[PDB]
Length: 314
Length: 314
Ligand SMILES: COc1cc(CNC(=O)C2CC3(C2)CN([C@H](C)c2cccc4ccccc24)C3)ccn1
Ligand SMILES: COc1cc(CNC(=O)C2CC3(C2)CN([C@H](C)c2cccc4ccccc24)C3)ccn1
Ligand SMILES: [Zn+2]
Ligand SMILES: [Zn+2]
Ligand SMILES: [Zn+2]
Ligand SMILES: [Zn+2]
Image 1 (tube, each protein chain N blue to C red):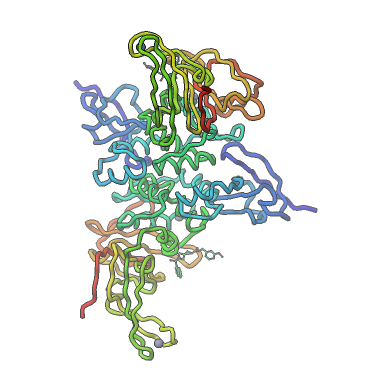
Image 2: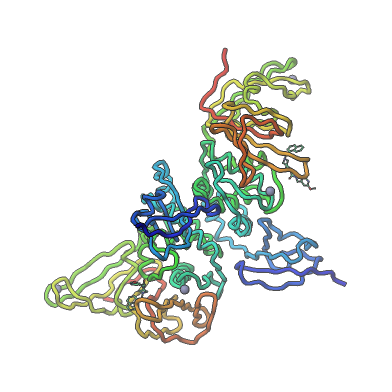
């Protein structure tokens, strides 16, 4: 016998069709290219959680590859379908202005997207893709619906599933214009010797291992390629911002030492991001809710700092 | 005494504030730059219809003029506020796929916007403004929410008020890339003589006075600048399409003679637009509703034709 599921298919997000789909075949073998909640489910077999959900059917068109590359800088023929189906969810989200910044109301595990949006409103940055920059322009004014849908598409993430704000910044900053961002590190191994690495681009602004920007300037531990544990320190930095990242741990945020930060309470499976910014005192933006603080001591994961140009003291 | 109205103000379209505003002053003198339903009401005094409506407050920012010019090709400092407040209405509209084309469900007098959207999906055209072209790209796939909000902003029109599809095409095609569109007319006055006018750009594709494209090729009446009634006929046309327009009157649409058309039933104050296209037979798209026809005889207002290059016979 055949075990089926009841689902709905649509091509306009208005008129639906009842479908009893066979779990023996993929959605692509049923309907063609199919998307659900911002994810491509073309080569995906039906699963019991899909019952009652509506599926977006968008047939492929080779003539649109040139256009999609112009606006979004992508060659993925599924980007359009995932962007539209994710936007069908984000346009219903609420974007309240908290602490003079655009935040996002709690919905579909967007508490990590809220932290990404709040940090981007405080660092000087521009994106190369025209559609991503126009959406970023409207998001800074309050209309962040298209912007979050783009961030979801660029990260190959699904509406509802949790994500890391650090991982998402990696995927997003590849389309930023960090061409003139430069970072010079001096790795000091006690077997191999001293070593200059000139990192540029997305790598010149992001570090993983520590939250303190002064810790990187003075010296932070790191395993050398020979196996031994070495030490590297920042020699020259040249960008508009830096983003320090580290796994969750109790970090103490002082006033005037940083630009903004993100914290994460919970295990690896489930947790809640909240955003901290420095204005006249420390603000904590938990979605649509705001708290005020002289200082914050919690599980910080990412910290942002302002920069123009730095050089170590000889 | 002072006569007031009860209204709501917001800066996020989520959190509202009750306001009792004085009709003696404008909304700008109350709150700053203020928008309502896609219209700038900054220098507008409160009126009894505004009771219960929510107003969008967006303060001015001179640093955004350069950005807004890049994405939208506009120097109007109110374009952003009118675009966002109009988009807050169009995202709730329904865009059903009728006859293989993206139409719009009846709402807020959008029956003229539906006719504009349906014609743009059948003529070969591209827009210069990047944000307008990306929205046009998504509208051709089904997501026309941002596109209609842009058309409303470019036309300085308000959500809910009726409009002409011909007038709206004029405002919209100024941002199209019709740089290589050329039209040559020969005006023949029986007092002044024969006269060549080389029309280019938005004027090379649009004519007002007749619906028949063969009537313009053969000869159509027109008052000369001397007062007498002359006659002009098309000598050379060089574009991807032409749009013939005329006030409402019974026109008989045959199969295979045109690309698509718009009709309008009613007086000058109120009326309903419906769209006719030619596929295997004549389709009539009245919003979310479709009728099929061997031919249509009704009050046609605008007709579109396909073109590549034309030259009159010597
Ligand atoms: C079998 O289904 C799953 C489901 C999940 C869902 N979870 C995620 O998507 C993760 C995205 C994070 C949760 C990882 N981020 C925090 C800040 C984090 C980073 C690095 C190390 C950590 C160590 C301990 C706790 C948190 C850490 C947010 C994951 C895996 N399998
Ligand atoms: C005092 O408030 C008003 C309200 C309106 C509302 N109406 C409009 O916005 C017009 C946009 C049209 C209605 C004009 N279009 C039709 C096709 C049309 C064009 C040219 C000539 C016509 C002659 C007779 C009937 C229709 C004609 C659509 C107007 C004025 N004052
Ligand atoms: Zn959440
Ligand atoms: Zn070593
Ligand atoms: Zn209507
Ligand atoms: Zn004359």
